[PDB]
Image (cartoon, rainbow, N blue to C red):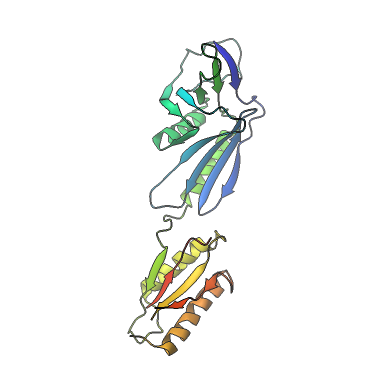
Amino acid sequence: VMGKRYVATPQQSQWEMVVNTPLECQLVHPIPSFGDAVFSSRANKKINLDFELKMRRPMGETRNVSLISMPPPWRPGEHADRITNLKFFKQFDGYVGGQTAWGILSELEKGRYPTFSYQDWQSRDQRIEVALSSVLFQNKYNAFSDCISNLLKYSFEDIAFTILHYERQGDQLTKASKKRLSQIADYIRHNQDIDLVLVATYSASQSLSERRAESLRDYFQSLGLPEDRIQVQGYGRVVISLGRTQ
């Protein structure tokens, strides 16, 4: 028997894309009284998706948690009907990632209501659930997917790059070195909490270096961001090396 079940009221299930970027797609569903069910995916080489049950009022050690499906806005009926089992967690801490997370999705679209079964409070008692309605889900999911498809296929897989100019003469950038720049610019721009650091560790020349540094300073001043994300640290190739930022 169930005592408490957080689920949103059939109408009131709002699904929102809180984040739509070539960097991270985040789909949210507030749980009517429990908290939010957040879905995230970020720019990376391999496809990814982690789910996070963002509790708003805590409980703090949840053991033997189960995952399943069932549309409840309706009347007298059984749960037994067709209750697909998704997974069991000896220990659940509000997180999920991988195929499991893709499940919760696969379900929701099917119309089903993924729900987390808890036996936390008191000891022996009714099941205190937490479900996610699949009301609007679909509209937004289609937005979620699109967002994922346009997700950059790389992460901080460009934290430190060494540009290789050709003919050695210096000033002319290679075909690739140019492909690595835009690449590095296509990221940078959508994340303005990260900055550029032009590194010349130092046979080249001071004359070359300088006009060779200006080149990117423009190359980037052209693309989008300005005069401050660029820092040209001197100490001992014009090697771009970005550190996080902060």
Q: Report the residue that reaches farthest toward the right.
A: 12
Count of labels in the image: 0
Residue 20 vs 163, above or below: the answer is: above
Image point 51% across, 36% down: which residue? 52
Please indicate whether residue 125 sits to the left or right of residue 46 in the image. Answer: right
* Image vertical order of residue 179 relative to residue 74, above or below: below
Residue at (40, 66) in percent of width and height: 160
Residue 127's spot in the image, x, y percent? 53, 15
Where is residue 93 drawn, in percent x and y?
Answer: 48, 32
At 43% from the left and 75% from the top, the residue drawn is: 199
Q: Nearer the viewer, residue 139 or 80?
A: 80
Give the answer, above or below, for where 97 lies relative to 172.
Answer: above
Residue 200 can be seen, yes or no: yes
Q: Position of residue 121 (x, y in %)?
A: 55, 18
Instruction: Please name whichever residue, 181 or 245, is drawn nearer the observer in this view of the structure.
Output: 245
Instruction: Please identify the quarter of the rendering in which residue 156 is found.
Output: bottom left
Question: Picture coordinates of residue 186 (x, y %)?
Answer: 49, 63
Q: Quadrant of the N terminus?
A: top right
Q: Residue 66: tell me if it is visible.
A: no
Q: Nearer the viewer, residue 94 or 154?
A: 94
- Residue found farthest to the bottom: 207
- Residue drawn at (37%, 72%) of the image: 162
